[PDB]
Length: 11
Image 1 (tube, rainbow, N blue to C red):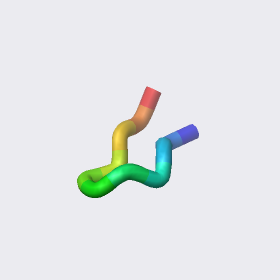
Image 2: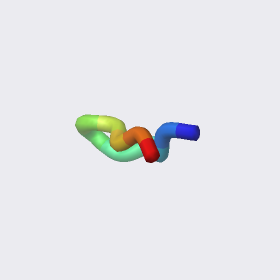
Image 3: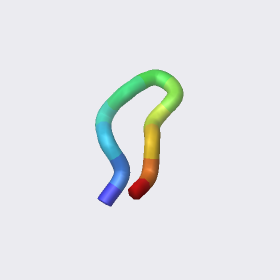
């Protein structure tokens, strides 16, 4: 899943 950061990060 992708984190909730700005910008968002996907693993």
